[PDB]
Image (cartoon, coloured by chain):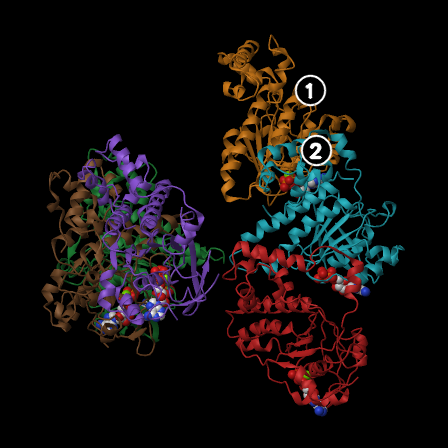
Chain colours: A orange, B cyan, C red, D purple, E brown, F green
Amino acid sequence: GPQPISRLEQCGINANDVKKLEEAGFHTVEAVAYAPKKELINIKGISEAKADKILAEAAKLVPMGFTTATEFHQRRSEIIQITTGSKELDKLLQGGIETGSITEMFGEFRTGKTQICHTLAVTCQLPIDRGGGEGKAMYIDTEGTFRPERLLAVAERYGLSGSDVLDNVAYARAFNTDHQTQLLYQASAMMVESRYALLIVDSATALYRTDYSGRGELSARQMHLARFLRMLLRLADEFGVAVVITNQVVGGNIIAHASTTRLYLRKGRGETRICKIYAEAMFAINADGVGD
Amino acid sequence: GPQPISRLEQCGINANDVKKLEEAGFHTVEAVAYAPKKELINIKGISEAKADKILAEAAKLVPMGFTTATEFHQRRSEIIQITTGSKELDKLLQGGIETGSITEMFGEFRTGKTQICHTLAVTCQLPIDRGGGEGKAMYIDTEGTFRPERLLAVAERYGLSGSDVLDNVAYARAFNTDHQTQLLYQASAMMVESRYALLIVDSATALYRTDYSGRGELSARQMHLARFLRMLLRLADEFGVAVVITNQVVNIIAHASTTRLYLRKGRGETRICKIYAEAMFAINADGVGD
Amino acid sequence: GPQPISRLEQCGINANDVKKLEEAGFHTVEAVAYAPKKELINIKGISEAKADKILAEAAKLVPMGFTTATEFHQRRSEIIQITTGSKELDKLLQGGIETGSITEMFGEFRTGKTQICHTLAVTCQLPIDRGGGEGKAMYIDTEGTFRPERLLAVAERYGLSGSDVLDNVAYARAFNTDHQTQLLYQASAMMVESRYALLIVDSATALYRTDYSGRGELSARQMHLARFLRMLLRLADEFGVAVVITNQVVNIIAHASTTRLYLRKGRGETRICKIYAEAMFAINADGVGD
Amino acid sequence: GPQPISRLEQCGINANDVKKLEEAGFHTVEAVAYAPKKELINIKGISEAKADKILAEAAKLVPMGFTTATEFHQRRSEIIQITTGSKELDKLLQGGIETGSITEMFGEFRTGKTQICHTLAVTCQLPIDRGGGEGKAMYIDTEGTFRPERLLAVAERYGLSGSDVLDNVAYARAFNTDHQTQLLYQASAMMVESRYALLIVDSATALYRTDYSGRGELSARQMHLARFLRMLLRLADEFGVAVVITNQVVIIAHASTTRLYLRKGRGETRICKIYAEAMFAINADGVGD
Amino acid sequence: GPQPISRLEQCGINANDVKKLEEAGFHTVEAVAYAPKKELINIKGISEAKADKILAEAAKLVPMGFTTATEFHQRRSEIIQITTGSKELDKLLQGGIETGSITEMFGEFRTGKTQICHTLAVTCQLPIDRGGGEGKAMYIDTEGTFRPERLLAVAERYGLSGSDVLDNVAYARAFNTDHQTQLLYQASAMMVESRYALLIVDSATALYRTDYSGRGELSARQMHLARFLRMLLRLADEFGVAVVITNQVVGGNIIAHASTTRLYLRKGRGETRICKIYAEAMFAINADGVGD
Amino acid sequence: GPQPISRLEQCGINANDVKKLEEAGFHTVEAVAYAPKKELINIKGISEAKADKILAEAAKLVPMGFTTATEFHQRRSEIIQITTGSKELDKLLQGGIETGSITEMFGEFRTGKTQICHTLAVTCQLPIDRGGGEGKAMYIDTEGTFRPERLLAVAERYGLSGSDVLDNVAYARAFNTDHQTQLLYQASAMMVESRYALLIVDSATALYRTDYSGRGELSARQMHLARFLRMLLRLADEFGVAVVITNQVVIGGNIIAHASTTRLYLRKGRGETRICKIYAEAMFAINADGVGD
Ligand SMILES: Nc1ncnc2c1ncn2[C@@H]1O[C@H](COP(=O)(O)OP(=O)(O)O)[C@@H](O)[C@H]1O
Ligand SMILES: Nc1ncnc2c1ncn2[C@@H]1O[C@H](COP(=O)(O)OP(=O)(O)O)[C@@H](O)[C@H]1O
Ligand SMILES: Nc1ncnc2c1ncn2[C@@H]1O[C@H](COP(=O)(O)OP(=O)(O)O)[C@@H](O)[C@H]1O
Ligand SMILES: Nc1ncnc2c1ncn2[C@@H]1O[C@H](COP(=O)(O)OP(=O)(O)O)[C@@H](O)[C@H]1O
Ligand SMILES: Nc1ncnc2c1ncn2[C@@H]1O[C@H](COP(=O)(O)OP(=O)(O)O)[C@@H](O)[C@H]1O
Ligand SMILES: Nc1ncnc2c1ncn2[C@@H]1O[C@H](COP(=O)(O)OP(=O)(O)O)[C@@H](O)[C@H]1O
Ligand SMILES: [Mg+2]
Ligand SMILES: [Mg+2]
Ligand SMILES: [Mg+2]
Ligand SMILES: [Mg+2]
Ligand SMILES: [Mg+2]
Ligand SMILES: [Mg+2]
């Protein structure tokens, strides 16, 4: 799928200019092509002639022209469409979470948004014919709640081995608003080496709340969240990873425009745990992930 | 050894600046690495270039990148699980107090939340095989209920030396709502000189309730207590220390407590403990175990 | 012991900022340290720079950090531990009333609660070796029952001079609810220059119930009583005075207490007490019996 | 500065040019000398050579060169130090309001800053021996709080004729923001005929808070107030007249040589901080108690 | 007295530039002179040179220079100082309400503020030698309480003819917040045309209270009220009318800086209707205006 | 004719916007003239220039400037002054209910406040010389007490044909709080469709008492009732229609005190002999044929 920068080297001065793109945040040739000229100019050590040469060579490897809608329909076909463990949720989402798009989640507290993230991180490693995209998840946590013991229980019901499933999953444990951004930098390098399917960013707004209490800092955090969200859209594009964002309610803001699908959750007086497409489906939290 | 900040000095670090970072609150290279660039700039006398250099070197002394989930699993199979006595009959906590995470406590009054804090303060200094933390406790009293005689009474139950239990506890009464905050700043300095396995706040809200009695304040009480809790998480993970908070019953103040523990008055001496599982725990003359 | 506020002066603008804090109630450097930035900046005439400076200088004088329990055990040892005049009652409180604690008292009426206060008032003057702390009483009366005739009568029982005994004791005779509040500020002013031991506030709640008119002020009355005891604990802790509260029966006055001495009744003259154990003591013309 | 622009006229000056320069705001040669080439070239009808010759003759009249520190100390020993009556009690300002400087005040409301301005307006007319300035004041009211009856009463306390106290005081209410600058220009014009000793602005920032309501014109207000303060500094420096500015507490930080903060005290007794304290009481006949 | 803009024509172009100032709000030459440059610039159709010419002609027309304090003292004399119908109030106010200054009023309800507004309106028509200033009142009502029969009764008490006292009094009946400002703009015309003495704004804060209930509109209503008060002060200074403002209590805030005097009222219980200069005085509402 | 809004459609009015204003709540040019620019802007689909033009054309068709007190006195000596019945003896209101101004009512229970509401609804139909309103009422029941049989009885007491007294009363029960506001919106058009002389609310606080019960809202009920009363004042002083509001007592000055220019508080006096005093005295009875004893 994705094509590394190493292919871009053609009189481009290897190992003196390729890394200047590597620490710039670009890790694939298509990432450079999908990057503006000004994004390459502001990088130190890249001249106007050299930046033009890189973009000219980048456009040669990846196609950025006009394609007919029939070609796009089949490209939008064969989408991985990883499952979610619940039959009703599977029917409601027309096959679960779709790759290449950010799927947000909402809730008040103890609504299962962290819980259904765990059952996704294991089901993304299932083969295509039985749901997920046989990849590896990249769970990122901010409010520390990652419990690998839960992955053992949910992997047991699907017949997967308990050892192999943990090797595929990657953990981040972000601590600051900025540290989330450099995690995506290390994410892009990791996406090239191995096939990945999920980019769970559980509690993607928890950090922004804790260290931006200043009333005059709203304009600062709005742009910071926009850059983080914008970097999520692109990262989903080259690699086709179903980015999942968990957010705290206590509906519609700068995070909404970037998002493709939302799955507002809350409890219920009866039968518990319904979902929305802010359509309703039935799901519940059992010992082994989600159930009916 | 959780990497003290003295190891960050280089030619450009200008170790006179280490004391400038030390007075800010960051006494650990993990603290500055986990500190955002925003609060490095807010420190007076630190420039944009200086802050970048501090963060750049702090990054290469601690693992700040990704890790495989199987590595994190065995890093969870190292929790101390400090013993408590009679509450963990059939192991409601599955081992004991969760180290590296706050364990908040509730109750109405005369329930026994303060009493097991005394027992927790003597258990954490027991050897690991018996259920201890092999480290010395830390008490931050807030209402003035600290009784060092109780520590001696429970010490003889486990056979530990009476003289060796009092010198281990680091007691500090909090007369103020802000005095709690800078006690934690003084705490991080003390956590690197020796090994502490338990931090206890006798009442995280007693002075917040009485000092902030104004009708208008309300909101001001929130982010002040939020900063108190956000530092408790900061001390919890870069030292691997168990934090116990007791509160009086009858962002938010409910997102930081990894574990909760509500308490009830049963029939007579039969104390009741519940989690928001229930167990029989008592308050004997020599501790909590029945 | 307590350090007078005048020592705080080091470029601190004498008689203009020290005097400004004098009417604020902060008459010792301990009071300044034990007070937040809030009411130091709420005092008119103090800016943010001055408030920070006076707090910084106050911190350097009194210790505010962490101390080992061994230091606190000795500190909580050698307490004055004022006697109560009754040997059976003496051992039941393992030494009688203890300083630094708001020892409340209960009853119905004619229960001896005022009687033992007068006995406790004469005995605060005794030397360490046989009871009291060689200090002066600071009786505060609301429901007028202070009869100095009793003090001279009990003085000859213990063999003390009947003239110097009344010279040491103070007398307030509070009238209004706001009057009780401002006496405590004046109490701290006169506290510094003399060794004081006892702070009887006899009938500390019967004055408020006089002002209790209608149901539309219960919220305000509790808040006023909240900071009345808050000052008392803020006054006993950093001056080491044995505050005694005498309430009448049939987070208010329940949390701030340290000991209670319910005074049920008996067989007419067989007065007894609780620690809400029983102690046998008689009430006669010369104070109360042993 | 008893050195008028009239004496600048010469054979080559073409004294009609003096009148033409007067409208620019310059009425003393000390004003043109202290003004750069920029402030003279922008005046219509003045050529480069004319400005050069004007500045050369101004330099030949007033000296701008260096001076020994002893002479500077001696000339700063000749400060009038207009008295107040209760603020100066216990020698808070070591004499009172000093001439040649801006003495900005503060206050929340009813703190007494207007009343002490009234007291100063009559104390400046005292003979220098008693603590006055031997010059007529100048009141620039903005919020309409001027009351000559209070001036007459306070003059009665100090024992002066009421008619001579009032007719010396000059009054002018300012309605517009630019009206304040025009009033300062007229003040510079009229400062040369008679010896003045005090300039009172009742509330310099009052008109800026109401004329410049919103729509983000903050920068305009900022440099307009900067120009006002620079004009006042130039006036005080060239004429040696004490300048007093009051401000309303809910720029003016670099020009306030002495800064005062008035805040409510106990009853009629009030406290005054030098942003260091004193008891000033506002009586029925002034401030001195 | 006040001088109309029609005298401003010296190559000022009548019916094309004078009318622009008239529709902008200014109706007298001193209104233009007491107005800043930008208040003339922001009006469409007036250039910088035209504004300079208008300001210069106004400045030579009216005197905006320095005046000796003796002249201002004699100008503080001959103030109309209209009476109020109560000898106690007459002595307390040192002659009653004074022209050129807003006299605010406070009260809970049924305190007599509208009643004494009515007696002021009737008594402002008296000749100089016996109280009022032989002018015309302009009672502006927001919460409809204007009762002309009360004016008839009180005028009969004072001996004035009942026909003329109605002929001189003017009524507004404001409905909206902007309607008050438009009413003052229209009131400037009657200021120019005829001699006027009173500008009652009875319940000047009732409309602002009733149509600004939104918690997010406090800044807007404060700015509107500030503009309204500044307009009242400029009108009073221009024409020397005794503006009286009636306010509803249920202490002090931004409104007193523009105000000159306040007459806080209270019920009084025994003998009732006691007032302050927030010094005290006692008045009584008879069937005929105010009395003892 | 209180100037219906349909006359405001000029070349620049875009008569679809006229219907937009009509559904907004304003049905007369007087309503939009007495309307601040703020709420016209908040009407979704009206631009700043369009709102300016609407206000400008509203201003030049209705008088909004100053008027001499003689003109206002003449415009006040034309109140319709609807009669009441038995209270005709010793006129306390100097003729009866004041037109164009709310006449609030009180009483504990069983007093008869609803009965004289029926009598007012029938007397609004009497000719002017007889003391009526020459119009049709609007009873808005909020407690389910409206009974057309009493209307028939009182109509035959004054000798009016029943079919002519029934066809004019516009009954509308309220099940809700916002239903009252919607009813006022609908009544705004009914005012211009035909002449109306009285508006009656059976209990303006009955629904507010039962729909809002929690301690939480309180202020919500407060400004909801404030908006209700403001709408009532606007309709009354725009359309020249008397408004009568009855309330449940068990009391004095509150939000509805400022809005009601007049009161009439009723007591269960000596049996059949009821007593009414304004917040004077008048004794009236409630017979089978209405009020007149
Ligand atoms: N093994 C399990 N069996 C049944 N229910 C569970 C299990 N684990 C968790 N739950 C329930 O699922 C919920 C998960 O909440 P969570 O999603 O972590 O909260 P948040 O959305 O605030 O992060 C808990 O409230 C818990 O009651
Ligand atoms: N020696 C003892 N024997 C039995 N019970 C005790 C003994 N000492 C203390 N307790 C009990 O332990 C409890 C401790 O209460 P504590 O937790 O300190 O109250 P708080 O929660 O208000 O701090 C008391 O209610 C008391 O009944
Ligand atoms: N000299 C005495 N002889 C005998 N009995 C006494 C003497 N003095 C006091 N008493 C008894 O002690 C009681 C004192 O009442 P007291 O408890 O002081 O009232 P309060 O309830 O206000 O404290 C009286 O009931 C009295 O019977
Ligand atoms: N004759 C007097 N006797 C006592 N106090 C007075 C007298 N006249 C004025 N004052 C006091 O002087 C103060 C004047 O306030 P002022 O400085 O005019 O307010 P502002 O600073 O807003 O202009 C008033 O608060 C008043 O209390
Ligand atoms: N003819 C009269 N005789 C005596 N008193 C009257 C007469 N008319 C009105 N009043 C009294 O004067 C007061 C006027 O109140 P008013 O000031 O109009 O209320 P608000 O302050 O709400 O406008 C009423 O309380 C009334 O009692
Ligand atoms: N024919 C009649 N004779 C005597 N009394 C009657 C007659 N008809 C009605 N009433 C009285 O009129 C009263 C009307 O009460 P009403 O005002 O409807 O109560 P509410 O105030 O709850 O609406 C009743 O209490 C009833 O006693
Ligand atoms: Mg969750
Ligand atoms: Mg307890
Ligand atoms: Mg007693
Ligand atoms: Mg003042
Ligand atoms: Mg009134
Ligand atoms: Mg009834």
Give the quadrant of the C terminus of chain D: bottom left
Foreground disc of the pair 2, 1: 2
Which residue is at the front of the view, C126 or C251? C126
For label 1, the residue is A194
From this view, report whether residue E187 is shown above or below residue E129.
above
Pick the front one: C45 or A196: C45
Relative to B127, F168 lies left or right: left
Secondary structure of the residue carrying numbered label 2:
loop
Subunit ID for the residue under disc 2: B
Is F238 on the left or on the right of A55, as rendered? left
Vertical side of D212 occupied by A141: above or below: above
**Which residue is drawn at the image coordinates 85% and 55% (left, top)?**
B164
Q: Please give the label number shown on residue C249.
A: none
> Among all residues in the image, which is located at the extreme right?
B159
CA distance separating discs 2 and 1? 38 Å
Image coordinates of residue D280 in percent, x first then y, are 41, 67
Count of residue discs: 2
Amino acid of disc 2: Gln
Q: Quadrant of residue F255?
A: bottom left
Q: Residue C173 location, x and y as percent?
A: 58, 81
Q: Is residue B193 visible?
A: yes
Image coordinates of residue D215 in percent, x first then y, are 35, 41
Give the x, y percent position of residue D138: 28, 56
Q: Residues within 10 Å of mark 2 (few under 14, many from 20)?
A: few
- Between residue A35 and residue F98, name the one nearer to us: A35
Amino acid tagged 1: Ser
Label 1 within 8 A of ligand 7 by Cβ: no
The residue at which mark 2 appears reads as B10
Chain letter of mark 1 equals A
Q: Is residue E45 visible?
A: no
